[PDB]
Amino acid sequence: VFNATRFASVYAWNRKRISNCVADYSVLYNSASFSTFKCYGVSPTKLN
Amino acid sequence: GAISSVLNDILSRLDPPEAEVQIDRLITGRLQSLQTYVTQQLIRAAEIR
Amino acid sequence: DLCFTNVYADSFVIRGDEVRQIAPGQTGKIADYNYKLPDDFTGCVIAWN
């Protein structure tokens, strides 16, 4: 979903259920690809 | 009024500038529960006296 | 009207969007690798283009 071809809009919403795997939340914050990565309920360091 | 009742659930989710606020809602809510038990038992101790 | 003992003077340069990073409490790119202020930091910074 970061390297996809086409994205949707706010009128037609895309949903993707992801489960049963092993992730890495450290690579989503140090890479210079975004500007706003602020969170609401969970701290970004404690996600791992 | 906090997020959860377990103190281990708030320290392992929140940053300590934010986790202090949810902990402080649990300290005040549990201090008034202890002061009601002591006050209600000081009148029962006078009735049994 | 009031004053303290002594003041400190730390000086560096940043980019245009990193003014928000020098602030007490949160993280970032500068706040994680380069320069971070504590939670009980009394004082303030001033920027100029």
Image (tube, coloured by chain):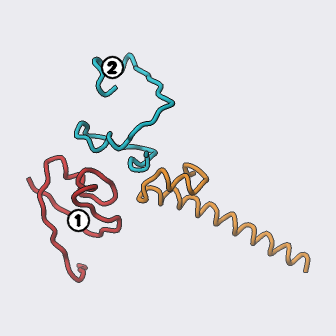
Chain colours: A cyan, B orange, C red
Alpha carbons under labels 2 and 1: distance apart: 42 Å
Disc 2 is attached to a residue of which chain?
A
- Which amino acid, by three-letter code, is at mark 1? Cys
Residue farthest along the left direction in this orientation = C49
The residue positioned 53% from the left and 59% from the top of the image is: B23
Of tags 2 and 1, which is closer to the observer?
Answer: 2
- Which amino acid, by three-letter code, is at mark 2? Ser
Query: In the image, B34: left or right of A26?
Result: right
Q: Position of residue C21 (x, y in %)?
A: 24, 53
The residue singled out by tag 2 in the image is A9
Number of marks: 2
Residue farthest along the front direction in this orientation = A22
Quarter containing the N terminus of chain C = bottom left
Crowdedness near tag 1: few (<14), some (14–19) or many (≥20) residues, C-alpha within 10 Å: few
Query: In the image, A15: left or right of A32?
Result: right
The residue singled out by tag 1 in the image is C44
Q: Secondary structure at mark 1?
A: loop
The circle on residue A41 is none
Label 1 near label 2: C-beta < 8 Å? no
The residue positioned 12% from the left and 61% from the top of the image is: C12
Foreground residue, A20 or B37?
Answer: A20
Q: Secondary structure at mark 2?
A: loop
Query: In the image, C16: left or right of C25?
Result: left
Foreground residue, A5 or A24?
Answer: A24
The residue positioned 38% from the left and 41% from the top of the image is: A25
Q: Position of residue C14 (x, y in %)?
A: 14, 54
Q: Position of residue C7 (x, y in %)?
A: 19, 76
Crowdedness near tag 2: few (<14), some (14–19) or many (≥20) residues, C-alpha within 10 Å: few
